[PDB]
Every structure is written in structure tokens, then in C-alpha cells.
Length: 330
Ligand SMILES: COc1nncc2c(C)n(C)c(C)c12
Image 1: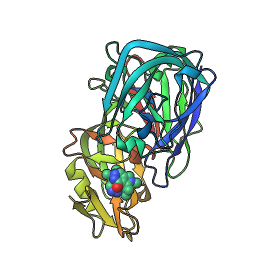
Image 2: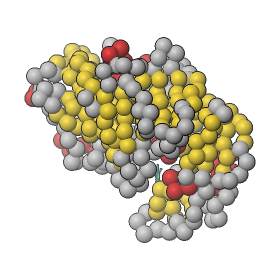
Image 3: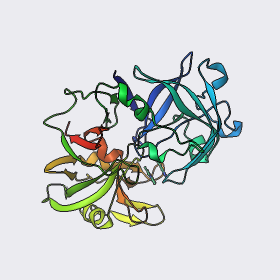
Image 4: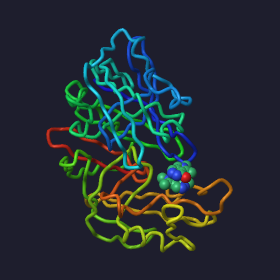
């Protein structure tokens, strides 16, 4: 089997991407944030505290003839941005782009933090990291990909995120029309539960490439590119007036600037992030200070190849017996 679904930016900044997912019988379609940095499929639901729902579409398990309470199971998650959610668990039929898993754990939120309530466009998350990170207790549950894997034509999924435009998540096949040149594959460590790999270096604009190992994660659920402070300082030094602002929470730059590109290494290959991808617009409405898309990972504890980086590539998440990541230009 295979599946193919379109993923769409939630806003004009590409803060996140949503992908429609069918849950239950008859289908209930929710728009979920596919997140290769976590491993829970959780949704706003008929059980979510009413004052914490503000425009999201909810899953109602009592209206699904295939939903079953997973007795005694609970879940609770906290994300790198300080947001959180928790609740109980059902199993139900879940389909993505024509690919169906029966008995998928669907984690129903009883509580969500304010940042989830405030984002009316995201109805929940669909985790695509390794199932060892799944938070369900006392019986840990498998991701949608993990459950689908054995049925797929090939044990892979691909992320093809758009810049200010729709893109695609495919399961079970590699669309050879979706990228240019060849796909360069690189080793993955699953020891922390992430799609963790080592970039071979970087360049800023038309500058020379610096060969240096940068260990980080491929995370579709993180908006920005978070890299070591040395690398980030070298980038922003090329932008007149750019500075790190503790009051704003990162590097800012004049909105009048034209940003340089940023290149990252994948083995001997190179992925070029155009400068425009690094512009996140005014820090507040009407401001002439703009927020940067490359930020320091210092004080996160891990480097994160988030959407800013991933959207410049066609990315293969290879879940073969020894997982690997592939990157191609597009
Ligand atoms: C204008 O965009 C922003 N402004 N201020 C802080 C931000 C943070 C922390 N992130 C991730 C974005 C996209 C920001």
C-alpha cells in the first residue's frame, strides 16, 4: 500500500503545516500537524475542556462505530516550545491520503495549553518520530508510520514541504518526479528517539563551505532552523543591522534587508536554503524589525533542522531495519 496527502501552511509565515487525516467510522476529518520530532497522535476532542477549544475541529469517539476506549491508558506531553496537552486514549481507524491503519491509538485531549487553544488551524498532532518516544502509559503505543510500515510497498515516508505553498507527505513510495538530481542518504541514530543525523557543514550566501560535523534532528514540527551559536553568528554577521535580542527572544534583522542563502551539507551533497525562507516577518504588527529563521540552539540541548531547512529539500524518512535519512534538492 501507499498513501499521499497534501500538507498546507497554516499561515503566511509557514509557522506550521497541516495535513487532513480521516479518523473513525464514518470518517471525521481533522487537520493535523505531522511532527517528525514526536511520537503521539493526539487530537482535540469532545473530551477537551470546553474553554480550551476555540475553533478547532474535534474528534468525537462516541460517533465512531470503530472507536474503542483503550482502558486505563493516559498520555501527557510537553514540547520544546513549552506547550503541553494530555488526556485518555482510544483505538480507531485512521487514514492518511488513502493509506489506512486499523487499531491506531488516537490520543484524545482532555487538556491543552494556551498556545494550542490559540491556534484554531491545528486540530492535533500526528507524531512521526520513533515509537520509543510515545507517551501513552501504562502501555506505550506505536506511531501511524510504525503501524503502517509492514503494509507499505517500501518502509518509508517522505516530506516535501512548500515555501509559502502546499506540499506533500507520501507513505510507502518515493516520487521520483518530486526532486532534482539524486537523493543523498545519511546515517541516523535512534538512541534519543529522533531522526538524528550529522550534517557535514555549512556555507553562508556565496561564501566558502565550512566542513564541520553538526549533529541534529530532522523535525517537521519545528518552524525554524536551530544551530550552534558559532554558525548562527556567522550567518547573521552577513546581514547589516542584525542582532540578537534577549527581549524579543532571538536574532532580529531590519525588514528592509535582503537575506543571504544558507547551505547545509548532507554527506558530499549540499542543500541551499534561499534567503527569503529565513524571513519570518515583523516581530509585531507594523514593526520594521523582522524575526530570523535561523536561531541559536544554545540552551535547547540539540540542533534542530526544522521547517526552514526541510522545506528546501525533498526528505526521505527511511524506516528500514537500519533507518536512514535522504535529502535531495528540488
Ligand atoms: C515574527 O515571528 C516571530 N516573532 N517573534 C518570535 C518568534 C518566535 C519564537 N518564532 C518561532 C517566530 C516565528 C517568531
